[PDB]
Length: 329
Ligand SMILES: Nc1ncnc2c1ncn2[C@@H]1O[C@H](COP(=O)(O)OP(=O)(O)O)[C@@H](O)[C@H]1O
Ligand SMILES: [Mg+2]
Image (spheres, rainbow, N blue to C red):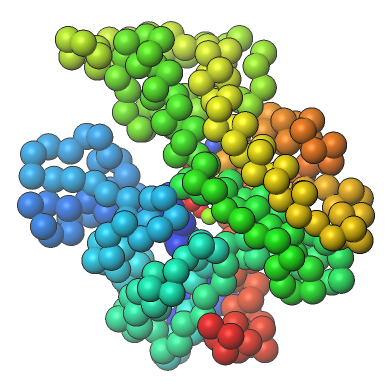
C-alpha cells in the first residue's frame, strides 16, 4: 500500500492516480474563496461557479494552461493531495505531475514546491501530450510516428512522438473554454440573452457539434439590456454555427503540425492517423472534421478524459521508468 501518486493537473479537471490502486480522485480544478480564505475546492466549488453570493468567488487557478494565481493554485493542489492520502500506506511519497507543455521553469518550480509542501519526498514532471499518448495506448517508445491531439479546457496540445521523445509539440489556447465562450457570445448576439459558463458547457455537451446538421433544447439566462430572467430555444444548427470558429482553430493547429513532419514519420501518420484525447475529443463530429481536413484516419481514445492520468499512472507503476522521470526533471 503506497502513497505514491500521479496528478493530472488540468486546466479544468484534476485527476489523481495512486500507485497500486488506480484513479482515486477526479474533480474540477476550481477553488471557492470567501472574503480571502479558501471555502471549498473541487466538486463543491464548481457547483458554485456563477452562483456565488456576496463576499465569495470561485476561481480556476490553472484556467488558460498557465498559473493565474500561484497561492490559490498551491492551495488547490495541496487540498487534493491531502484528500487522497492513505494513513495505512508507506511514506516518502513519489509524485508525478502532468503539466502543460508550455509550462515555464517558474510554473514548474511552483508545482514542484506545492507538492513538497503537501508532503511529497520527490516530484517528477511529464508534459501533457506525452502522458496523453501513453494513456491512449500509443506506442510512444517504438521507432514509429504517433500523433496525439489532446483537447482540454484551456488548451489543445498537439504532438508527434517517437522513441520516447518529442518530434513536434505545440499548444494553442483553444479548447473547451473557447467553445463555451463562443456559445455565450452566440446567445448574446442572436438571442439577447446573457448565459453563464455552466449553461454554456451544458449546451456544448447536449447539442454541440463540429458539423452542422436540428435537435433543440431550452436555455435560460439574463436579458442582455434589461436584466430579467428569460428562456430561449437553441438548435444544433445554431450550436454548430456558434462553435465553428474555435473548431476551425483546433483543426488549423492540427494541420500546422502535419506540415512539421519528417518523411518516414509522415509515412507512419498516413498509416494510422491521429489519436484524439481530452474532454474536447468528446465534441460530436470533431473527429470527422479533423479527418476531412487532413485526409487522415482519426480515432477518439477510449476514456479520453482519463488518458493523461492513466498515462502518468503507467509511468508511476514502473520504478525504472519513474526513476528516469524524476532524474530528468
Ligand atoms: N461531451 C462533451 N462534449 C464537448 N466537450 C466536452 C464534453 N465533455 C467534456 N467536455 C469538455 O472537456 C473539457 C475538459 O477536458 P479535460 O481534458 O478534462 O481538460 P483539462 O485536462 O484541461 O482539465 C471541458 O471544456 C469540458 O466542457
Ligand atoms: Mg488535460
